[PDB]
Image (cartoon, grey):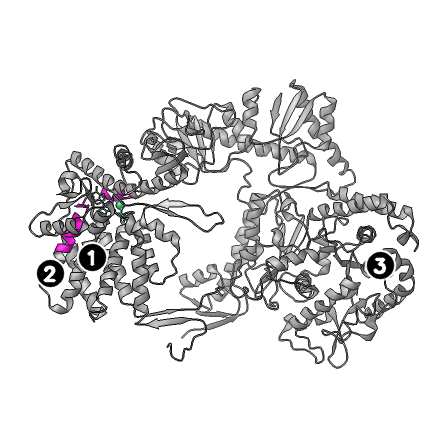
């Protein structure tokens, strides 16, 4: 195919530069986000060449790979791998990128050993099957005795926020992340926790609101605070209805009848508001816009009117007040109203927001992130999003494993025990699978500046004879017990790091020909 | 001072409105009834007792027509147009209007 | 029936008219020396509307080319398919107009327009039912304003009841050719709102930025200028030249374009605008082409539709598509952007379609409709007319041929009355 | 043993004469027009039915209404 090429502007390579470009392009992705892994790793700042560059600092490996725009074909497999890891569990996107790159780096070492690439695939399938049994047998469940499960949930949020910008804020941001999912008391919808980013103040000034915050302040001549009110929301049109009959006009003979029709239009718009206040309410939230004619009617009756909050803002108010959407007002005995105590307006960062203090059945939260710059607020929002998504799945799957390098040495030990019970064809591929699992505590140990040649060697000697909870202590720089220090991760997060990296390395290693087509508008 | 968000102009609705003229005297019933329409709006304003009107800036239809401007000048009423929709919060808190 | 005789009068009218018949002869498959190369009644039925069939199968276009210049119309004599017209449809003029309105009416027009009316009479013999006439000219030209204004007045002595669809090339607000361009634009329009009913506005210099930015042309010229103008000319006369479900001829277009007969200045245009290399890398759907005509990137004149309000909207599509999606897409814009449309018209955007594809493009739509975009362009013409007439600059060029100082006074009073005519509903 | 019906008609609900304007004055007669547009199409389907023509062939398109009617009456169309 290179000799006597039958292509126009397209090129290809077979078994010489195919695996060469696949191993170079995938290691350079993994070596890029290598410095961001661990609780002592640095962060990246992403910039463009111009034309609203919109600089966005991120430490999470999914947000780095989704914005760099790699031109390598085999590197897009690892870029899409970190996107699925953020969409499923929301954590380990950096850990699954280095692990999939360390598998292909050990596969580059098997180039000169003349090992068949299908032997490495069949050797890694038996290695990944033994690695699933190491995490499944070491998972710690939590059913009853809930005072130890809430302590276990703070160890999950303490491990996730340690590898982010919120380093010296674990005394505050752990309570902001555990109690946010604990106030859901149900499914992890991940949209009732509305994060509001406001400039001014430090990250210690951020807090979790006991009620709910909103924008689009209360009318013009309406009351600003009503105590012991009944909140009724809506999703209906207020004025300029044009009610659902396309092709309907007002064909009259004189202009005196147009004055009678427009008075009949305002009488039906007034009668719609009169059906709303028969419930006995004091606040009104409409998803659509409220014009001036129903605004005067709510202001004359002493009723609030919040106009055009959000499409998903009426869903959070329905989960924090315990009511319903109620888009049709014709049955006051079948419409459930919300409950609150204070609807006072608070000022956060020279902006008046509507505080719904003292609400009943409040299965929704509002995190008020305050930072020094907008770059910190964009990073702390993604750092909190990577912490709330794991706790939303830890309450659904209570199985937890010991992180901090302890889980990877347990997975590498089960592969090494079965590497000695195999013939020599697939045993060399299983030894490279166990060395790549030991690189994940090696990257964490070397990012702090510790002796990674000795600490991982002490972890391999500890896990070889007992010590199932022995891991890497990044606080002092030694080997400690992970059950005492409280460094644990979720089982489903660590399983998706192991499983998705083994499936993505299976695709790139099986590629022997990269036939790229002719691009458009590139000359 | 009174803040008015109504448009003192010809009668029109949100729906499509048309006038059918099929008679000789029907053209007289269009112009003279439009003058009697806004005269009932000016005399409703004049009998209230206000001297300063603040009309909100309308985009869809005309807020203050030329026919409505002449009746308000004979009632000795100062009329101010083009008040923005984002400025009505500052006006109602300062003067005390609704 | 419903025959229309075409009159291409002026220097700019023959340049547009040379490529005006290139689109009709290619879409209908009419051979210039053979008989026809059609396929069905979509192309072969409407031949007799714009062509008169001779004995033997040869088709002759109903076209009259008027020019006060021998050298300009010789390109349409034996050039790009110019040998297909009648030999008496080549009325030359040995005396040039000189970009003067008074010279084309009283000096050149007193001896030629009796012979130009004879060519319309011979063309009307083969018309069993004359529908109307079209007139493509320019305001900044001598023959377009001389033999376009006097020709449109003498044609009403013989055809007082027939409709008229004039095509006017407006001058540009960006560049200027001569200082008598506000004089020629004011005098030609002053006798155009008198007894006509349709007039478009095409700016040629405003299309140089469209070809530079959208059509990707580095050095444009007059040949690349008239290519997309011919696509706009063929978009209006699409249902007139091809049958279909939405039957709307020029008689149905004269009523449903203007609620009032005086405010008959439209803004033509079409969509999409693709280059010679980026055309195949672009898909064309129904809401893609319908939403492109309302923006300012698809205007043939130097105007701004983002600060105006339309009155009547008509659109003709090219290709077999579902036309029920056109009305549902445009009705959603009339509720969110009601300050740009009419408040009492339930169906502002009209629908038209055919089953004949255009040349080059796969799908294509055209934009025909009036708005207040001509109001801001008529103020700049009367502003230049006010400063030149108050100093009485170059008035001896006009008053020496038969004009007077009271002629420009009445031409200034009614043209400023047209500014207040558009200022009511703005 | 089927019977084939060869048609040159539209089996859609939106069959319009392209110039019809149904001006109504009341809501009692407005609902009667919408019921008439379905009864025009359903009367054509009753002519295809009660004849044995289980296979329908037409050069003009058929909408979702007449497609689901033949599926309930165990008839094929194209
Ligand atoms: N307190 C701690 N002690 C030891 N290791 C830790 C601690 N906190 C975090 N880590 C390690 O740092 C790593 C951070 O990985 P991370 O970049 O969050 O992966 P992802 O990008 O997939 O979320 C984890 O694998 C975890 O083992
Ligand atoms: Mg993490």
Q: Where is residue A69 in the image (x, y as percent from the top left)?
A: 39, 56
Q: Quadrant of the N terminus of chain A?
A: bottom left
Residue at mark 1: chain: A
Q: Is residue C339 above or below residue C29?
A: above
Q: In this view, does A301 lie above or below B10?
A: above
Identify the residue position indicated by label 1 in the image.
A436
Judge from the rendering whether residue C415 lies leftward or rightward of residue C317; answer left or right.
Answer: right
Helix, strand or loop under label 2: helix
At x 67%, y 69%, the residue is: C23
Badge nearest the viewer, 2 or 3: 2
Q: Is any atom of residue A37 visible in this view?
A: yes
> Who comes first in sequence, dot 2 or dot 1?
2
The dot on residue A418 is 2
Which quadrant of the structure image shows residue D8? bottom right
- The quarter of the image that holds ligand 2 is top left
Q: Are marks 2 and 3 in contact (CB under 8 Å)?
A: no
Label 3 residue SS: helix
State the extent of the magenta-drawn residues as a range.
Answer: A389-413
Task: Name the subunit of mark 2.
Answer: A
Q: In this view, does A208 lie above or below C257?
A: above
- Same chain for labels 2 and 1? Say yes or no: yes
Locate residue A171, reporting x and y percent.
25, 32
The x and y percentages for residue D7 are 52, 70
Marks 1 and 3 sit apart, C-alpha to C-alpha, by: 89 Å
For mark 3, name the chain.
C
Q: Nearer the viewer, residue C152 or D64?
A: C152
Q: Are marks 2 and 3 on the same chain?
A: no
Crowdedness near tag 3: few (<14), some (14–19) or many (≥20) residues, C-alpha within 10 Å: many
Q: Where residue A31 sits: x, y (%)?
A: 29, 55
Q: Is residue B3 left or right of residue A216?
A: right
Q: Name the residue under label 3.
A: C146
3D distance between C-alphas at marks 2 and 1: 16 Å
């Amino acid at each position: 195919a290179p000799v006597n090429i039958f292509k126009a502007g397209a090129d290809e390579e077979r078994a010489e530069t195919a695996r060469l470009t696949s191993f170079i392009g995938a290691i350079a992705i993994g070596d890029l986000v290598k410095s961001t892994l661990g609780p002592k790793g640095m962060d990246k700042i992403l910039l463009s060449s111009g034309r609203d560059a919109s600089l966005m600092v991120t430490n999470d490996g999914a947000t780095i790979l989704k914005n760099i725009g790699v031109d390598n074909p085999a590197a897009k497999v690892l870029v899409d791998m970190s996107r699925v890891q953020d969409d499923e569990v929301g954590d380990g996107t950096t850990s699954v990128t280095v692990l999939a790159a360390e598998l292909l780096r050990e596969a580059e070492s098997l180039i000169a050993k003349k090992i068949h690439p299908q032997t490495i695939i069949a050797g890694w399938r038996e290695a990944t099957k033994a690695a699933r049994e190491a995490l499944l047998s070491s998972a710690v469940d939590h059913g009853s005795d809930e005072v130890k499960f809430r302590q276990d949930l703070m160890n999950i949020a303490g491990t996730t926020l340690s590898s982010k910008l919120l380093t010296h804020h674990k005394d505050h941001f752990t309570k902001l992340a555990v109690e946010a999912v604990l106030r859901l008391k149900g499914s992890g919808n991940l949209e009732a926790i509305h994060i509001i980013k406001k400039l001014g103040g430090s990250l210690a000034d951020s807090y979790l609101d006991e009620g709910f915050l909103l924008d689009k302040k209360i009318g013009v001549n309406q009351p600003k605070r009503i105590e012991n009110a009944k909140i009724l929301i809506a999703n209906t049109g207020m004025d300029t209805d044009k009610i659902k009959i396309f092709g309907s006009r007002v064909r009259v003979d004189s202009t005196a009848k147009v004055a009678e029709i427009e008075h009949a239009e305002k009488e039906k718009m007034k009668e719609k508001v009169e059906r709303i206040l028969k419930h006995g309410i004091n606040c009104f939230i409409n998803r659509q816009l409220i014009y001036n004619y129903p605004e005067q009617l709510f202001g004359a009756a002493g009723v609030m009117a919040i106009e055009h909050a959000d499409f998903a803002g009426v869903e959070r108010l329905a989960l924090v007040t315990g009511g319903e959407i109620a888009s049709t007002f014709d049955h006051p005995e079948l419409v459930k109203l919300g409950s609150c105590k204070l609807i006072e307006e608070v000022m956060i960062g020279e902006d008046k927001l509507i505080h719904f203090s003292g609400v009943a059945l409040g299965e929704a939260c509002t995190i008020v992130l305050r930072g020094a710059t907008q770059q910190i607020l964009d990073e702390a929002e993604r750092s909190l999003h990577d912490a709330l998504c794991v706790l939303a799945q830890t309450v659904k799957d209570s199985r937890t494993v010991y992180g901090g390098g302890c889980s990877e040495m347990l997975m590498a030990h089960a592969v090494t025990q079965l590497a000695n019970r195999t013939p020599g064809k697939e045993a060399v591929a299983m030894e490279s699978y166990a060395k790549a699992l030991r690189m994940l505590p090696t990257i964490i140990a070397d990012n702090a500046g510790y002796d990674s040649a000795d600490l991982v060697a002490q972890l391999r000697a500890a896990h070889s004879e007992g010590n199932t909870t022995a891991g890497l202590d990044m606080r002092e720089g030694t080997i400690g017990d992970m059950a005492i220090l409280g460094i644990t991760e979720s089982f489903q997060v660590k399983r998706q790091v192991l499983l998705s990296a083994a499936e993505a390395a299976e695709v790139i290693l099986r590629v022997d020909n990269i036939i790229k087509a002719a691009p458009r508008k590139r000359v | 001072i009174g803040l008015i968000q109504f448009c003192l102009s010809a009668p029109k609705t949100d729906m499509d409105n048309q006038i059918v003229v099929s008679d000789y005297a029907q053209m007289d019933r269009v112009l003279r009834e439009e003058r009697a329409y806004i005269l009932n709006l000016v005399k409703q304003i004049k009998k209230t007792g206000c001297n300063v009107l603040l009309i909100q800036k309308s985009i869809l239809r005309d807020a203050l027509s030329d026919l409505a401007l002449h009746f308000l000048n004979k009632m000795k009423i100062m009329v101010i147009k083009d008040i923005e929709r984002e400025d009505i919060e500052f006006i109602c808190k300062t003067i005390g209007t609704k | 029936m419903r025959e229309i005789v075409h009159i291409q009068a002026g220097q700019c009218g023959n340049q547009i008219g040379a490529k005006f018949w290139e689109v009709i002869s290619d879409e209908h498959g009419i051979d210039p020396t053979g008989t026809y190369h059609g396929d069905s009644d979509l192309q072969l039925d409407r031949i007799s509307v714009y062509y008169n069939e001779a004995t033997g199968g040869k088709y002759v276009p109903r076209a009259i080319l008027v020019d006060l210049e021998p050298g300009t119309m010789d390109s349409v004599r034996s050039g790009p398919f110019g040998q297909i017209f009648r030999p008496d449809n080549f009325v030359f003029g040995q005396s040039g107009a000189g970009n003067n309105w008074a010279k084309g009416h009283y000096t050149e027009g007193a001896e030629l327009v009796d012979s130009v009316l004879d060519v319309v009479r011979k063309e009307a013999e083969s018309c069993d039912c004359l529908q109307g006439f079209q007139l493509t000219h320019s305001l900044g030209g001598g023959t377009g304003s001389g033999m376009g204004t006097l020709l449109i007045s003498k044609i009403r002595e013989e055809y007082p009841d027939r409709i008229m669809n004039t095509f006017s090339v407006v001058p540009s607000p960006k560049v200027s050719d001569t200082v008598v361009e506000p004089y020629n634009a004011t005098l030609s329009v002053h006798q155009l709102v008198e007894n006509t009913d349709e007039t478009y506005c095409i700016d040629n210099e405003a299309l140089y930025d469209i070809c530079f930015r959208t059509l990707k042309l580095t050095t444009p010229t007059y040949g690349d200028l008239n290519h997309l103008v011919s696509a706009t000319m063929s978009g209006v006369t699409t249902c007139l030249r091809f049958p279909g479900q939405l039957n709307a001829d020029l008689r149905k277009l004269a009523v449903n374009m203007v609620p009032f007969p005086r405010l008959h200045f439209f803004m033509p245009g079409f969509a999409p605008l693709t280059s010679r290399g980026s055309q195949q890398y672009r898909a064309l759907t129904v809401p893609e082409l319908t939403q492109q005509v309302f923006d300012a990137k698809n205007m043939m004149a130097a105007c701004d539709p983002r600060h105006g309000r339309y009155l009547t909207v008509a659109a003709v599509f090219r290709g077999r598509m579902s036309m029920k999606e056109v009305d549902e897409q445009m009705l959603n814009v009339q509720n969110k952007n009601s300050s740009y449309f009419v408040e009492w018209i339930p169906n502002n955007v009209k629908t038209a379609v055919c089953d004949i594809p255009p040349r080059g493009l796969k799908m294509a739509v055209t934009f025909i409709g009036n708005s207040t975009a001509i109001q801001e362009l008529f103020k700049r013409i009367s502003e230049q007319f006010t400063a030149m007439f108050r100093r009485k600059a170059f008035l001896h060029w006009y008053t020496g041929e038969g004009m007077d100082e009271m002629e420009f006074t009445e031409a200034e009073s009614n043209m400023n009355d047209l500014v207040s005519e558009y200022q009511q509903y703005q | 043993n089927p019977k084939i019906a060869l048609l040159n008609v539209e089996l859609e609900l939106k069959a319009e004469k392209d110039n019809a304007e149904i001006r109504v004055h009341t809501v009692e007669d407005y609902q009667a027009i919408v019921d008439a547009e379905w009864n025009i199409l359903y009367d054509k389907l009753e002519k295809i039915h009660h004849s044995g023509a289980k296979v329908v062939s037409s050069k003009l398109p058929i909408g979702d209404v007449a497609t689901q009617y033949f599926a309930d009456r165990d008839m094929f169309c194209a």
